[PDB]
Amino acid sequence: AVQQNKKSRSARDMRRSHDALESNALSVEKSTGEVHLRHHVSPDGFYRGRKVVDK
Amino acid sequence: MKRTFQPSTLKRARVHGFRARMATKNGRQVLSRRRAKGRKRLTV
Amino acid sequence: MRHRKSGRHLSRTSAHRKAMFQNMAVSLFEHELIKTTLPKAKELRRVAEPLITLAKEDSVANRRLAFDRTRSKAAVGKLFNDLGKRYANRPGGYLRILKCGFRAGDNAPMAYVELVDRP
Amino acid sequence: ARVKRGVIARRRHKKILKLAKGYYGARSRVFRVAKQAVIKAGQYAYRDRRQRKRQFRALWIARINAGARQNGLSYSRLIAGLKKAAIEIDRKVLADLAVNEKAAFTAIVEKAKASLA
Amino acid sequence: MEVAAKLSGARISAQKARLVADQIRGKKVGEALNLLAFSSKKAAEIMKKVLESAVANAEHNEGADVDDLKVSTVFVNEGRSLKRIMPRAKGRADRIVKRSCHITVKVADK
RNA sequence: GUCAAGUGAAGAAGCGCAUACGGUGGAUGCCUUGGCAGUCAGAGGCGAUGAAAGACGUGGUAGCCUGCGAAAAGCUUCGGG
RNA sequence: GGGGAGUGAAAUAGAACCUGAAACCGUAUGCGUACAAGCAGUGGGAGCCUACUUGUUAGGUGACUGCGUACCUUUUGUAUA
RNA sequence: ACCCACUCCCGUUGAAAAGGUAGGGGAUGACUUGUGGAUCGGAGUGAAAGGCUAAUCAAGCUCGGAGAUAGCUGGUUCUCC
RNA sequence: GGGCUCAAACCACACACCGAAGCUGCGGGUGUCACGUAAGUGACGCGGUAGAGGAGCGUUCUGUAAGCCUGUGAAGGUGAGUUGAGAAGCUUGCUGGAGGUAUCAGAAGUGCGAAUGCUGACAUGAGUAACGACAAUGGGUGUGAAAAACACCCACGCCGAAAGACCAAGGGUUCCUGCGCAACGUUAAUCGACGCAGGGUUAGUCGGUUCCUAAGGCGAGGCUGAAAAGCGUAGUCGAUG
Ligand SMILES: [Mg+2]
Ligand SMILES: [Mg+2]
Ligand SMILES: [Mg+2]
Ligand SMILES: [Mg+2]
Ligand SMILES: [Mg+2]
Ligand SMILES: [Mg+2]
Ligand SMILES: [Mg+2]
Ligand SMILES: [Mg+2]
Ligand SMILES: [Mg+2]
Ligand SMILES: [Mg+2]
Ligand SMILES: [Mg+2]
Ligand SMILES: [Mg+2]
Ligand SMILES: [Mg+2]
Ligand SMILES: [Mg+2]
Ligand SMILES: [Mg+2]
Ligand SMILES: [Mg+2]
Ligand SMILES: [Mg+2]
Ligand SMILES: [Mg+2]
Ligand SMILES: [Mg+2]
Ligand SMILES: [Mg+2]
Ligand SMILES: [Mg+2]
Ligand SMILES: [Mg+2]
Ligand SMILES: [Mg+2]
Ligand SMILES: [Mg+2]
Ligand SMILES: [Mg+2]
Ligand SMILES: [Mg+2]
Ligand SMILES: [Mg+2]
Ligand SMILES: [Mg+2]
Ligand SMILES: [Mg+2]
Ligand SMILES: [Mg+2]
Ligand SMILES: [Mg+2]
Ligand SMILES: [Mg+2]
Ligand SMILES: [Mg+2]
Ligand SMILES: [Mg+2]
Ligand SMILES: [Mg+2]
Ligand SMILES: [Mg+2]
Ligand SMILES: [Mg+2]
Ligand SMILES: [Mg+2]
Ligand SMILES: [Mg+2]
Ligand SMILES: [Mg+2]
Ligand SMILES: [Mg+2]
Ligand SMILES: [Mg+2]
Ligand SMILES: [Mg+2]
């Protein structure tokens, strides 16, 4: 099964009207002022104030 | 699945090599044709 | 449906699933802090936490039960010599699952699994 | 001796596409689609020079009908009255009076009513 | 002023890279950098490098402040494709297009 | 002011047309390194004194082309310059 | 891979390099577009926007509405499924 | 084992231009197999199916006659009177 | 179709009106005749496939042209305006950076949307199917810009008449080391049968060569055949022995 008619560029872009990416939930640590994913250990290795991975 | 090319350099030489071509008159014609066209490789 | 069912398939056979979580729990007892996927870390709770509960009572039968479920002499020794005594007064919750980011290779949600008292 | 077609062909295709400006999709971008649209638009435009005269006359007659019925006459009776009394004001001007100069249109309708009887 | 950085021949599709570009268009550079640092897309790793290279151009060639800059213009253009052959089931040969794109980020204080 | 009835902009997930600026692509123009066809001549053969055609070598530095042949991008001599 | 600097008459002549068309893909702006049925135009036509010539103007868009079933070929005959 | 290919299912833009999984037949013989060799285009070879002769067979492939022939199909390009 | 019934039905009569690219009006073009030895007037025409007849536009080249235009900007490209009945012409902004060609003639590879046309580029499908045996992974450490895939360690799993080790054929440097990651690898890659460079293969006894022959080949003379050749003796090759 295949198209009988080439899909128009308007119709192609209309299907893509649901393709937009969403932004993640970003939080800021208070011990360091560092940006991290909400509910995730910070890239430096802190979660809710304390260092957990210690690099 | 066995395919048509089963290489044997000895069989290749004895069927298509330079001395196989030079042995006959139609073989010499192949070498004349391939020299006239300018083939870099003459036989195999 | 999976109404009220427990467990994660994790795209594995049950033999491989059993072998992997026994490997992971042994690794967690040795290192006290490991990184794995978040789905594996959440299912590792139900395997590794009953082993620490068992290790609180040191006996020949409990140690043999530990060895049947870990198949590791080092893990059995650590459970009854260190972890069983360390968590004697802790009523469960010996593990901590902390979400790290995502794996670079496949964007898999990562988690840190650490023993609660000291990792 | 040898004649390249590139320059002349590009000029031809650009004239067509310039005429297809404002058309949807391939009708303004693709030559062999735009060529059909430019021809069809030309067929319509020729036919609608004829249709415009019909459309406007139907619009004048409808407005004259509305204006004359406000004055107690139907369109057909007003035209017959405008022939009995030799008034040659055409329907384009009559429809302009019926909208913009209502006192002038009333005077004409009264002149048609008197002529009928 | 407006400063730009351009990455030509980014080995990713223009369609894929435009999803990330639509997220950072019109944003302050600091916010856009934090969005790109935590995105799961491959285009965000590439886009973040172009964005911070544009920020560096604005701070060296023009002497600006990162806190005054915002992403004024970002667009992704299609680049050169690479042509490849993939075998199919019955001797059929299929052409693979390996798409690349040009990523232009412009920062401006204004 | 309250209520009722009537009327009603702006707020586009995306899309269209126009315009501007790009990208891709490599048309067009202009150009020529190479061809095509003649005209007038030349030469009308080369080879067991080893041909046509090659292989492998040959250079300060890897490869390929050109030349050359263990005397190997060349040796001797006679002229030109 | 770029941004400056510099070279150059010219670098959007920067080595995939003269010119640099079209398809095709974008970004920006203007107008239109979420109660509406079909070859997508054409006739009429409001509003909005822009520019001066300041409304009998030019450009862009175009609500709403009349009419309207591509082209080629082949055929007695084709919107023709 | 090896040779084979009876059934089903899968696969049918396949992992595969003939396969796979599960079953199946022969398995000291008119057996299977390696290396080398002989026979070929109105010719070969055929425990015979018009089978096979390099994924091509009621007469292989390749070049030439050759731009075969085609009362057939398709296509045939600027303007106006 | 809505709806319609002393009709918005049917029968008869009458007066109106609507209605086409028909007719008339107004302006314009053109054909043929006639008058004009003129510009032009008059009359009648002017839908059209196959097809006949007539009149033109434009493109490339040659002559006109050792001319004329052109770096104070050619051709080409891209907009705007304007002229003609049309093919089209002309003027100009920008781009471009060295060529172009008036006029009138002469020659044609002279005009493209179709031919399941040919070549290249790029779309749609669609960021979809798929990522090639369902033997299987988990963790720690290192390195690195970056690690699910690289290296190491601890576990787990798979083959084991092979998924291990060889000889032959076939391939030909893929072998090892250092450096490296664009492309290649159906993902990433620091890794590689990938890129750059260097290194590496040592025989009286292994295998060839050499000796000997099988099938079969070639084959001095020879016999045969229009030619080309065919066959074959002496011989000489030819391993799989
Ligand atoms: Mg439950
Ligand atoms: Mg899965
Ligand atoms: Mg089992
Ligand atoms: Mg939007
Ligand atoms: Mg200068
Ligand atoms: Mg130049
Ligand atoms: Mg260029
Ligand atoms: Mg609406
Ligand atoms: Mg619709
Ligand atoms: Mg109009
Ligand atoms: Mg209609
Ligand atoms: Mg019929
Ligand atoms: Mg019809
Ligand atoms: Mg059809
Ligand atoms: Mg249909
Ligand atoms: Mg049986
Ligand atoms: Mg039969
Ligand atoms: Mg066959
Ligand atoms: Mg025959
Ligand atoms: Mg003939
Ligand atoms: Mg023919
Ligand atoms: Mg009338
Ligand atoms: Mg009329
Ligand atoms: Mg008429
Ligand atoms: Mg007239
Ligand atoms: Mg007529
Ligand atoms: Mg006619
Ligand atoms: Mg020219
Ligand atoms: Mg064309
Ligand atoms: Mg045609
Ligand atoms: Mg689909
Ligand atoms: Mg799906
Ligand atoms: Mg899938
Ligand atoms: Mg695989
Ligand atoms: Mg990388
Ligand atoms: Mg093996
Ligand atoms: Mg190696
Ligand atoms: Mg890769
Ligand atoms: Mg290598
Ligand atoms: Mg013989
Ligand atoms: Mg003899
Ligand atoms: Mg011998
Ligand atoms: Mg032997």
Image (cartoon, coloured by chain):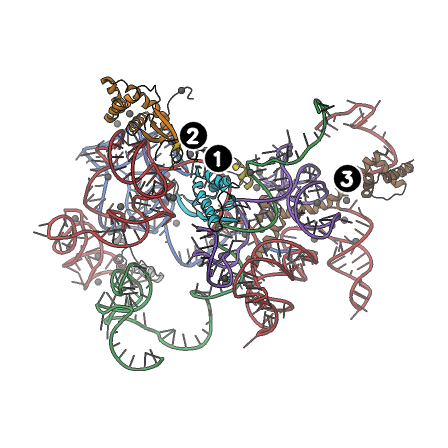
Chain colours: A yellow, C orange, D brown, E cyan, F green, G purple, H blue, I red
Q: Where F4 falls versus I84 (above or below)?
A: above
> Which chain is disc 2 placed on?
A
Residue under numbered circle 1: A23
| Helix, strand or loop under label 2 | loop
Q: Residue extending furthest front?
A: A31
Amino acid at circle 1: Ser
Amino acid at circle 2: His
> Which chain is disc 1 placed on?
A
- Residue F23 screen position, x and y as percent: 49, 50
Quadrant where the N terminus of chain B lies? top left
Residue under numbered circle 3: D59
Q: Nearer the viewer, mark 1 or mark 2?
A: 2
- Residue F54 screen position, x and y as percent: 29, 62
Q: Where C14 falls versus G3 (above or below)?
A: above
Task: Tell me, for residue D3, which label it has, or none.
Answer: none
Q: Are marks 3 and 1 in contact (CB under 8 Å)?
A: no
Amino acid at circle 3: Leu
Residue under numbered circle 2: A39
Q: Where I170 falls versus H24 (above or below)?
A: below
> Which chain is disc 3 placed on?
D
